[PDB]
Image (cartoon, rainbow, N blue to C red):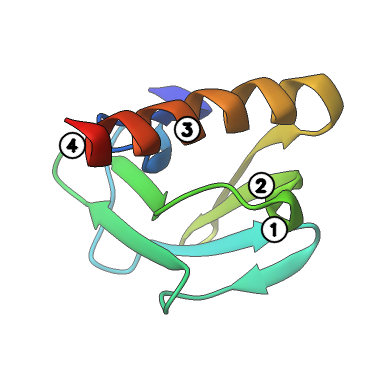
Amino acid sequence: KSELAVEILEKGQVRFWMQAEKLSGNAKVNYIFNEKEIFEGPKYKMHIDRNTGIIEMFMEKLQDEDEGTYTFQLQDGKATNHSTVVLVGDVFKKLQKEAEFQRQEWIRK
């Protein structure tokens, strides 16, 4: 298992992911950004692999507005895990610079 982590992918896409030990078909994840539930949509893509326990949310990019706290609220029935990455201040700027560089370099190359 691994708590919530963020990384930037080759195109500068953002990957939030954590690993549960096992997920039942009933496992559910509340994706939380600055204490607001966020949903699969124009901005986020969510995936749960119930086999691997890998829960991951993807963004295309990190806008200034994306600074904040990201939480995955995992519920498997009674079972209840939250994991949080605080992408604020310098942490956010650095991650954003990386994501912007990779997004820029993808389009450049």
Look at mark 1 in the image and give the residue it sits on: 33
Cα gap from disc 3 to disc 2, whole angstroms: 17 Å
Cα gap from disc 3 to disc 4, whole angstroms: 26 Å
Mark 1 or 4, nearer chain start: 1
Q: Say which amino acid is labelled 2.
A: Tyr
Cα gap from disc 2 to disc 4, whole angstroms: 21 Å
Mark 3 or 2, nearer chain start: 2
Q: Which mark is residue 70?
A: 2
Mark 3 or 4, nearer chain start: 4
For the point 25% across and 34% down, the residue is: 108
Cα gap from disc 2 to disc 1, whole angstroms: 5 Å
Q: Is residue 25 left or right of residue 72?
A: left
From the image, state whether disc 1 or disc 4 is nearer to you.
1
Q: Who is closer to the viewer here, 34 or 14? A: 14
Local crowd at mark 3 within 10 Å, few (<14), some, or many (≥20)?
Answer: many
Q: Secondary structure at mark 3?
A: helix
For the point 72% across and 28% down, the residue is: 93
Q: Are marks 1 and 3 in contact (CB under 8 Å)?
A: no
Q: Which mark is residue 99?
A: 3
Q: Which mark is residue 52?
A: 4
For the point 79% across and 57% down, the residue is: 34
User: Where the N terminus falls, by quadrant?
Assistant: top left
From the image, state whether disc 3 or disc 4 is nearer to you.
3
